[PDB]
Amino acid sequence: MFKNLIWLKEVDSTQERLKEWNVSYGTALVADRQTKEGGLYFSFLLNPKEFENLLQLPLVLGLSVSEALEEITEIPFSLKWPNDVYFQEKKVSGVLRELSKDKLIVGIGINVNQREIPEEIKDRATTLYEITGKDWDRKEVLLKVLKRISENLKKFKEKSFKEFKGKIESKMLYLGEEVKLLGEGKITGKLVGLSEKGGALILTEEGIKEILSGEFSLR
Image (cartoon, rainbow, N blue to C red):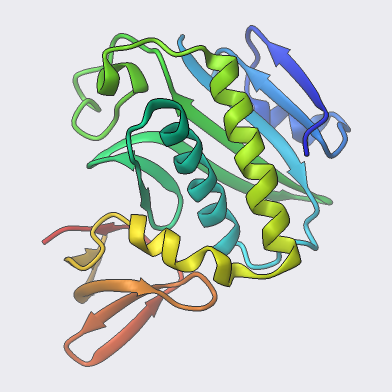
């Protein structure tokens, strides 16, 4: 589990910080706001050896965030392959993973209580407040997320990605629908699920294609 929080009122970037400072596993670095309000941001360190497949990891992290936000709010949430958490076609939480030298650094942002969603993004972004008409205690959100991440990641080390696949798929946006790759006019087809290694499976004219990266959309 986590054992230690470092809570900032503001900082440049929680990821940035975890690169420069030699924090320890079990520490979450949390910020109220990053400098490039009502949002929740935090980063932590994983063992880079424990998570060599880096499509599976962000997906289990996203699963965890979605489980947590639903426990708290009762609203169910979707997973975008390969990494964010959505309510409908709107992003509520970002999930990020960076190998930097010796470290695996995980970054997570959740839109909790922000009041004003800029005109340009409001079509593709949202907050818990927008969805529920209610403010939520940001630390209780954080705790619940950290607890689901601990739990899921532990099961993930003990067994495998198989304990998560179908849950992930069943939450995937555009699941079962027809999609294309962004700026890759070649691949179109139905989004049918995930491969063993976390890849997206598209049933194309000429059969199943496994995508190991890119961005999907409806048709």
